[PDB]
Image 1 (cartoon, rainbow, N blue to C red):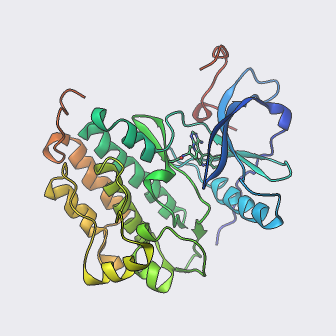
Image 2: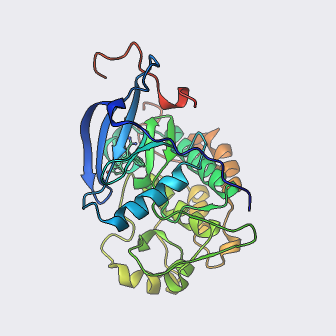
Length: 307
Ligand SMILES: */C=C\C(=O)N[C@H]1C=C(C)c2c(-c3cnc4ccccc4c3)c3c(N)ncnc3n2C1
C-alpha cells in the first residue's frame, strides 16, 4: 500500500476559547467553541468531542484510531479532523457544523424541507461515500445520525469510530464482536460480519430511507435479533409516502442479497443528480413549491483555513 502522509495536528489548550457544551449522548459529549491559532487573526468555529466515560487506556486507543482515519480524509462532503488536544482523555477537534446532524434536522424541519433539498443531500452523501471508496475506506456506520449539516445546502459525513482501511488487494473486512447498528447493516454483515463498500451502500439505502421518512426509525418496533430473519424472508423497509417508485427502487436496489448487484456510489451520484434536476417528478411533498457572538470580524470557517 501507499504511505499515509497525513498530518496529525496537535492543538494547545490555550488555543480554544468560548467552549460551551453542545450535546451529550451515545456519541459521548460534544462542545462548541472557537479555535484561535496563535498569531493568525482568525477565529475558527469548532466542535470538540470526548468520551462520557473515564481516562481508560482503551478509550484513548479507540479515540486515536478514529483520529487516524479522520486525519486522513479530505473531501467537501467528509468531515476532517482539524486536530487533537492531548488532555487526559484525548479530545477530537473538527469543524463546527451549526445545524447539527441531518437526522435531527429533518425531524425538526419536516414541514419546510423540499424535494430539492432531499435529493441534493442524497447526491452529497453519495459523493462523500464515493470519496471514501476511492480512499479504500469502509465507513461501517453510515446513517442519518452520522451526517452533519454545515448549511441546509451542504452536508458532510462524519463518525469514523468503526471505519476500516482495506488493503491494496483486500476486498472485505471480517470483524469480530461488538455493538453494531444492526438496523443499518447488510445481511452478510449480520450473518458473517463481512463489510465492504457494497455493504456501506446498504447502509446508504437505509440512510436515504431515513431522509424520505423525515426521520423515522428503521424497523420501528422489531427488536434487533429479528432483523436477520426478516431480511432473509425478503422483507425490506417500506416505500415512503413522498417517494415515487423511481426513488424507492433505488433504495430497494441498495438492499439486494447479492452485494455486487447493488448500485455503486458513483452511480447513486449520477442517478440522484438526474433526479435533482427535476425534483418534483421524483418526490411528492405537500407545499414543495412553497418551501454567533460578538467575535465575527475575524471568524473563518474551517473550509477557508488551509494548513
Ligand atoms: C445526529 C444526532 C446528534 O445528536 N448529533 C450530535 C453529536 C455529534 C457527535 C456532533 C458533532 C461531531 C461529530 N464528529 C466529530 C469527530 C471528531 C471531533 C468532533 C466531532 C463532532 C458535531 C459538529 N462537529 N458540529 C455540530 N454539531 C455536532 N454534533 C451533534
